[PDB]
RNA sequence: GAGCUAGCCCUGGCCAGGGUGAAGCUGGGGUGAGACCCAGUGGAGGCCCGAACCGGUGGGGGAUGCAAACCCCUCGGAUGA
RNA sequence: AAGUCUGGGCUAAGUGGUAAAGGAUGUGGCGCCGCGAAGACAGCCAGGAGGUGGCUUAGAAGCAGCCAUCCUUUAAAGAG
RNA sequence: CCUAAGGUAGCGAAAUUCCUUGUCGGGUAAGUUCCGACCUGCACGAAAAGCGUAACGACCGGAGCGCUGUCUCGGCGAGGG
RNA sequence: CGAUCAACGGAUAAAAGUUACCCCGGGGAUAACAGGCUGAUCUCCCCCGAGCGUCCACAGCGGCGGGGAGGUUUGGCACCUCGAUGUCGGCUCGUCGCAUCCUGGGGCUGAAGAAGGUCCCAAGGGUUGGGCUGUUCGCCCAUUAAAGCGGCACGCGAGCUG
RNA sequence: GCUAGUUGGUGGGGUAAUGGCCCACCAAGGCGACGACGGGUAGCCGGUCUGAGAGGAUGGCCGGCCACAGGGGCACUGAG
RNA sequence: AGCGCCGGCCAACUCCGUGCCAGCAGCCGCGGUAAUACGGAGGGCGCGAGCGUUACCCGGAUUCACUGGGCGUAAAGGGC
RNA sequence: CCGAGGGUAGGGCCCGUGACUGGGGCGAAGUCGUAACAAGGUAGCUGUACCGGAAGGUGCGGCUGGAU
RNA sequence: AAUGCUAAU
RNA sequence: GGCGCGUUAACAAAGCGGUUAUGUAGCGGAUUGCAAAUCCGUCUAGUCCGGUUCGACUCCGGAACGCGCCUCCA
């Protein structure tokens, strides 16, 4: 459950460290984003000389949430952070590495290159 | 263009007191040329020196075809002579600058009320029950440019609408009068430049009784005829080099 | 009518505890003598924190009230005009 | 309360029972001309042509813009 | 030209600026407020003092961190009614 | 005979201000809110067809003029209310109109397709979250099918805010 | 101006081996205008280039030494 | 067989073209209608499988002066 | 235990950059004046102070690198 | 008493 | 919008019912190597429209433009 004002850590190597959600790109008026959803976000903290910089407005897909995601098999999964991978308007990652595990829901939702690059899919 | 009346701005370049004196020579050269063209001349701005010349003169050339001919005189004009301000008999190279511009319009400015949006609303500040319930404040929006003017100066919406439209017009006017200036300014700089001894389009060498227009290589030796106004030979050679410049391909 | 309130006059009373550590003093250093430096001691102040006490900052309640100005939280002063 | 009263006409819009410029093969009544079996009006049947364009235009050459719109087999065919 | 003489230093869109959300810069994803500038100061200005200033303030602005039922957006529970 | 007793039937021989510290008697005889009447202003819709649109008045437009509708604005008037009809914005809760923002159905198009323009029908439902400012309004950010405009005492303070 | 393993001691760990190298404790010392500390820059020398010499500049090839082996830390094995 | 150069420093000069233009340039300077200084040409000077240029080091620099400089008025005696 | 490093917070130095602002060097021509060089037309210069569009002026004291 | 004189060997 | 004041030549600015304002500039001359400064001379006028009067820049009325002041209780 990500919404405007929500901070997310960045699970890639674009140079962004913290993005702040400003929109849930999910119809007219989605209240929340979960794993596999895309947000528009402001870049609140970045490391020097990265792809993206502080103040940029970027797009990202959510890859981990602290609110547990439930699964049709009756199970659930929960992460210690809210994390996202910065993408372009074609949904492809903009960095070349993805740090940490990601939800298997991303595979189902066409974020295959991200699933590819993640060290663990859970 | 070619057929409209023209304005000529003669400025003194490098040369000091004698640049202004040469500018006076170019001034008499064009007033007397104009008579030998039927063109009508009137001074619009003059700035004389006590030694006899001008640091700047502006004059119009009222005649059906003035820009077509005078337009070749724009540029830096170089004189080399022993100046009347010189006392050791030396030859000084000095410059005057000629600017040739088509006589602008004067077109009046009114508002196209179809590209204007008027918002009315309640005003801010004191008034009691009146200011609470009255749409006295006005905003006027110039829809193309986007610039707005607001007014709650009075208690009346109609007076604030009138005053707001006035200020909006006055401001769009200054915007129009300023882009016109930036075109006028850059154009002048394309013709007059810095006025340096280079940049010359023509030399009027008094020692060697020569006049050379280094744009086409034309050189006559009727320097007294040139300075008295007989510039038709030079223009034509430019005019003919102009058409031979339109030979494609 | 100054048994409310305001000012002044006379005569009394009150201010838990904790903190900071001025001058001075003493010693040491320094010097021609000094200034001054350092340590210790010392205990100054419309100094600090905080009860009583004096207040009344923000909020909530109260609003035919418990109350014709109150109640709860919070907050200012608290050796000084 | 008192006529589903009598006679003549109009309206088809519930107009009556909420309005203007203006628009209209709504309907009914007057007119005033015109064309008709010298076969009218509508339809169909053809013919509707030619020197072919003149100015303008690479063609605008019957079917852009300009200038007038000359004449034939004839019953008519206009350079439209 | 006029005045008794024509606003100096410093400051300035200000507790002062009507036009005005002036313009530029900063901060914000986005800033009528804020801060830094510019100066055509409607209508600053030198003890109705001018411009600054450590410390102080239950004074009035603007921002960030922390944290939150303020809010998305409400849920449940307690007691007095 | 002495009057700009000119406020000219001329209060004294002799007279200016201020009150947001205000007070009393009065008035809806008289203003400010809201209603009402009106509709100049405002908003919308038509008539005319000069001209634009390469061509072509009418795809889209409409010179100079003309006729209306609405009753959101600014006014005019002063009719209930001055022994009181609480006045902005926000919040909350809606409900209605339709001159329709979206979604549905159309005709025309200067409609190839896709996407638009324009007009017609249509009010069932929908019509986002933020930055600025008390703001209404407006601008901006990120989105959206869309981010409609209006009436209800500019809806709603014996419902809250202030 | 610098300094808390800082400077010295005692005792021990460690090594092939001395040592605050490491540790526990004791003492309050250690260093600096003869430039400590900090900042900048540099691998060093035999040589090499220049120069009358003194000096300056430099350290590529070759020889000697050091340092490093993607960026860091670590030890194992072993005569090393 | 090529490349640099031919105002002065510096060895090597005339003609034309250009007319403060085009350009040369290490310094001082050339070029504004008779330019050994710009561009070509002829001729000349220097080197030659090379010739020039740019960067940098030492030299000239006795211009950081130990060798081997200075401070009245040139930069330089500290106010005492 | 130490520990590569990662993280949190606060300092220090350095570089680049910034609305605007300050003066500085330069220029074959501009505006104002004419302070200095002659006793430069008020000897100059000087530290400092105050003032003035500007060079500058004036006060106080110093110097001669001052004329006759 | 009384200000000034650009710029080409 | 109201009230007040004004419009004069090249600029600035006055008086006045009949009539060279004035300053500076400009123009001619002098002086100066030249230019300034200076000296002798000299010159260009009343915003528009309508009235009054023998006669209007001058007085009255209005128009345009400029300036100064006011626009408050809601
Ligand atoms: K009042
Ligand atoms: Mg991570
Ligand atoms: Mg990261
Ligand atoms: Mg940042
Ligand atoms: Mg930033
Ligand atoms: Mg990425
Ligand atoms: Mg001279
Ligand atoms: Mg409108
Ligand atoms: Mg209002
Ligand atoms: Mg306000
Ligand atoms: Mg008031
Ligand atoms: Mg108030
Ligand atoms: Mg009203
Ligand atoms: Mg008492
Ligand atoms: Mg008592
Ligand atoms: Mg006592
Ligand atoms: Mg006490
Ligand atoms: Mg105590
Ligand atoms: Mg105490
Ligand atoms: Mg303490
Ligand atoms: Mg105590
Ligand atoms: Mg003590
Ligand atoms: Mg003590
Ligand atoms: Mg004592
Ligand atoms: Mg002592
Ligand atoms: Mg003591
Ligand atoms: Mg104490
Ligand atoms: Mg105290
Ligand atoms: Mg206290
Ligand atoms: Mg304390
Ligand atoms: Mg306290
Ligand atoms: Mg008490
Ligand atoms: Mg009390
Ligand atoms: Mg009290
Ligand atoms: Mg209280
Ligand atoms: Mg509170
Ligand atoms: Mg209360
Ligand atoms: Mg209360
Ligand atoms: Mg009460
Ligand atoms: Mg009661
Ligand atoms: Mg209480
Ligand atoms: Mg209590
Ligand atoms: Mg309490
Ligand atoms: Mg307290
Ligand atoms: Mg207390
Ligand atoms: Mg206290
Ligand atoms: Mg106490
Ligand atoms: Mg006492
Ligand atoms: Mg019947
Ligand atoms: Mg009958
Ligand atoms: Mg009908
Ligand atoms: Mg009908
Ligand atoms: Mg009916
Ligand atoms: Mg009807
Ligand atoms: Mg003032
Ligand atoms: Mg003064
Ligand atoms: Mg002063
Ligand atoms: Mg000032
Ligand atoms: Mg300002
Ligand atoms: Mg501002
Ligand atoms: Mg201020
Ligand atoms: Mg002010
Ligand atoms: Mg303002
Ligand atoms: Mg304002
Ligand atoms: Mg703004
Ligand atoms: Mg910004
Ligand atoms: Mg930041
Ligand atoms: Mg801004
Ligand atoms: Mg705010
Ligand atoms: Mg500011
Ligand atoms: Mg300004
Ligand atoms: Mg003041
Ligand atoms: Mg005051
Ligand atoms: Mg005063
Ligand atoms: Mg201040
Ligand atoms: Mg200070
Ligand atoms: Mg302060
Ligand atoms: Mg302070
Ligand atoms: Mg205080
Ligand atoms: Mg206090
Ligand atoms: Mg206070
Ligand atoms: Mg904040
Ligand atoms: Mg925050
Ligand atoms: Mg916070
Ligand atoms: Mg709650
Ligand atoms: Mg809400
Ligand atoms: Mg409950
Ligand atoms: Mg209960
Ligand atoms: Mg009178
Ligand atoms: Mg009377
Ligand atoms: Mg009277
Ligand atoms: Mg009478
Ligand atoms: Mg009387
Ligand atoms: Mg009397
Ligand atoms: Mg009286
Ligand atoms: Mg009174
Ligand atoms: Mg008051
Ligand atoms: Mg008051
Ligand atoms: Mg009172
Ligand atoms: Mg008072
Ligand atoms: Mg009273
Ligand atoms: Mg009273
Ligand atoms: Mg009263
Ligand atoms: Mg009363
Ligand atoms: Mg009464
Ligand atoms: Mg009434
Ligand atoms: Mg009456
Ligand atoms: Mg009213
Ligand atoms: Mg009323
Ligand atoms: Mg009213
Ligand atoms: Mg109302
Ligand atoms: Mg009313
Ligand atoms: Mg009513
Ligand atoms: Mg009506
Ligand atoms: Mg109407
Ligand atoms: Mg109307
Ligand atoms: Mg209509
Ligand atoms: Mg057309
Ligand atoms: Mg058409
Ligand atoms: Mg129209
Ligand atoms: Mg009408
Ligand atoms: Mg109408
Ligand atoms: Mg109404
Ligand atoms: Mg009506
Ligand atoms: Mg109404
Ligand atoms: Mg009214
Ligand atoms: Mg009304
Ligand atoms: Mg009323
Ligand atoms: Mg009446
Ligand atoms: Mg009332
Ligand atoms: Mg009653
Ligand atoms: Mg009643
Ligand atoms: Mg009542
Ligand atoms: Mg509604
Ligand atoms: Mg409809
Ligand atoms: Mg639709
Ligand atoms: Mg549709
Ligand atoms: Mg289509
Ligand atoms: Mg298409
Ligand atoms: Mg359509
Ligand atoms: Mg609907
Ligand atoms: Mg919105
Ligand atoms: Mg914020
Ligand atoms: Mg807001
Ligand atoms: Mg707003
Ligand atoms: Mg607004
Ligand atoms: Mg859209
Ligand atoms: Mg759509
Ligand atoms: Mg209301
Ligand atoms: Mg409303
Ligand atoms: Mg309400
Ligand atoms: Mg209330
Ligand atoms: Mg309310
Ligand atoms: Mg109510
Ligand atoms: Mg009520
Ligand atoms: Mg109620
Ligand atoms: Mg009620
Ligand atoms: Mg209030
Ligand atoms: Mg309040
Ligand atoms: Mg140890
Ligand atoms: Mg050690
Ligand atoms: Mg010890
Ligand atoms: Mg040593
Ligand atoms: Mg390094
Ligand atoms: Mg190195
Ligand atoms: Mg070395
Ligand atoms: Mg050697
Ligand atoms: Mg040597
Ligand atoms: Mg090397
Ligand atoms: Mg390494
Ligand atoms: Mg190694
Ligand atoms: Mg390594
Ligand atoms: Mg590598
Ligand atoms: Mg490695
Ligand atoms: Mg050579
Ligand atoms: Mg030679
Ligand atoms: Mg050469
Ligand atoms: Mg060289
Ligand atoms: Mg030349
Ligand atoms: Mg020649
Ligand atoms: Mg020559
Ligand atoms: Mg030659
Ligand atoms: Mg040479
Ligand atoms: Mg040559
Ligand atoms: Mg060889
Ligand atoms: Mg040497
Ligand atoms: Mg050298
Ligand atoms: Mg020596
Ligand atoms: Mg020497
Ligand atoms: Mg010297
Ligand atoms: Mg001495
Ligand atoms: Mg560590
Ligand atoms: Mg670390
Ligand atoms: Mg500057
Ligand atoms: Mg002088
Ligand atoms: Mg002097
Ligand atoms: Mg002189
Ligand atoms: Mg003098
Ligand atoms: Mg002098
Ligand atoms: Mg004398
Ligand atoms: Mg002095
Ligand atoms: Mg003075
Ligand atoms: Mg003399
Ligand atoms: Mg003079
Ligand atoms: Mg001068
Ligand atoms: Mg002289
Ligand atoms: Mg000069
Ligand atoms: Mg000279
Ligand atoms: Mg006059
Ligand atoms: Mg004038
Ligand atoms: Mg006068
Ligand atoms: Mg007079
Ligand atoms: Mg005169
Ligand atoms: Mg003269
Ligand atoms: Mg003269
Ligand atoms: Mg007359
Ligand atoms: Mg007249
Ligand atoms: Mg007259
Ligand atoms: Mg007149
Ligand atoms: Mg008049
Ligand atoms: Mg009042």
Image: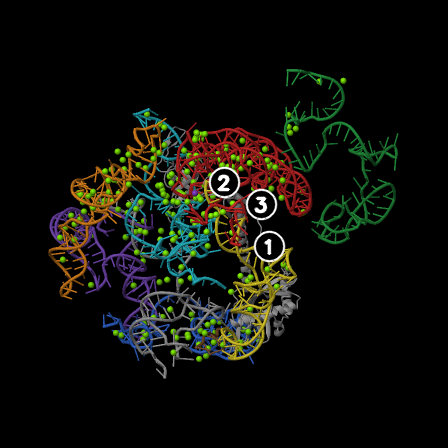
Chain colours: C orange, D green, E cyan, F red, G purple, H blue, J brown, K yellow
Question: Which label's residue is closer to the chain start, 3 or 2?
Answer: 3
Q: Determine the CA span between mark 3 and mark 2.
A: 26 Å
User: Does mark 1 fall on the same chain as mark 2?
Assistant: yes
Q: Which residue is labeled 2 in the image? A: B134
Nearest the viewer among E30 and J4 is: J4
Q: Secondary structure at mark 3?
A: helix
Residue B114 disc label? 3
Question: Which label's residue is closer to the chain start, 1 or 3?
Answer: 1
Counting from the top left corner in percent of width and height, residue B127 is at 46, 42
Position of F140 with respect to F53 (left or right) is left
Chain holding disc 1: B
Query: Which of the 4 image quarters holds residue B249?
Result: bottom right
| Residue A27 appearing in the image | no
Counting from the top left corner in percent of width and height, residue E64 is at 36, 44
Residue B107 disc label? 1
As drawn, C67 above or below A95: above
Disc 2 C-beta below 8 A from ligand 9: yes
Chain holding disc 3: B
Chain holding disc 2: B
Position of E80 with respect to F88 (left or right) is left
Position of A73 with respect to C15 (left or right) is right
Q: Secondary structure at mark 2?
A: loop
Q: Determine the CA span between mark 1 and mark 3.
A: 20 Å
Q: Secondary structure at mark 1?
A: loop
CA neighbours of label 2 inside 10 A, class few (<14), some (14 to 19), many (20+): some
Counting from the top left corner in percent of width and height, residue E10 is at 37, 58
């Amino acid at each position: 459950m990500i919404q405007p004002q929500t901070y997310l850590e960045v699970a890639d190597n674009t140079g962004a460290r913290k993005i702040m959600c400003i929109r849930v790109l999910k119809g007219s008026n989605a209240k929340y984003a979960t794993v596999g959803d895309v947000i528009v976000a402001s870049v609140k903290e970045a490391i020097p000389r990265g792809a993206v910089k502080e103040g940029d407005v970027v797009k990202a897909v959510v890859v981990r949430t602290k609110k547990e995601i439930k699964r049709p098999d009756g199970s659930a999964i929960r992460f210690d952070d809210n994390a996202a991978v910065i993408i372009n308007n074609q949904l492809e990652p903009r960095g070349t590495r993805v740090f940490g595990p990601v939800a298997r829901e991303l595979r189902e939702k066409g974020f295959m290159k991200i699933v590819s690059l993640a060290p663990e899919v859970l | 263009m070619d057929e409209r009346d023209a304005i000529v701005e003669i400025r003194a370049g490098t040369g000091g007191e004698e640049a202004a004196l040469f500018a006076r020579d170019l001034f008499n050269m064009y007033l007397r040329f104009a008579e030998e063209m039927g063109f009508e001349t009137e001074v619009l701005d003059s700035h004389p020196t006590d030694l006899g010349g001008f640091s700047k003169v502006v004059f119009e050339v009222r005649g059906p075809g003035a820009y077509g001919t005078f337009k070749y005189e724009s540029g830096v004009h170089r004189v080399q002579r022993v100046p009347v301000t010189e006392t050791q008999g030396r030859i000084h190279t000095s410059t005057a600058t000629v600017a040739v511009l088509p006589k602008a319009e004067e077109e009046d400015f009114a508002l196209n009320m179809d590209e204007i949006r008027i918002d009315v609303m309640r005003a801010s500040g004191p008034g009691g029950q009146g200011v609470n319930t009255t749409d006295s404040a006005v905003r006027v929006v110039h829809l193309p440019t986007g610039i707005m003017v607001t007014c709650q100066d009075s208690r009346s919406q109609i007076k604030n609408r009138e005053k707001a439209l006035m200020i909006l017009r006055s401001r769009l006017l200054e915007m129009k009068r300023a882009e016109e200036a930036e075109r006028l300014r850059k154009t002048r700089l394309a013709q007059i430049g810095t006025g340096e001894r280079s940049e010359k389009i023509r030399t009027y060498n008094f020692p060697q009784s020569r006049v050379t227009d280094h744009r086409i290589g034309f050189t006559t030796h009727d320097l007294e005829g040139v300075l008295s106004g007989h510039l038709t030979p030079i223009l034509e050679a430019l005019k003919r080099a102009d058409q031979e410049r339109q030979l494609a391909a």
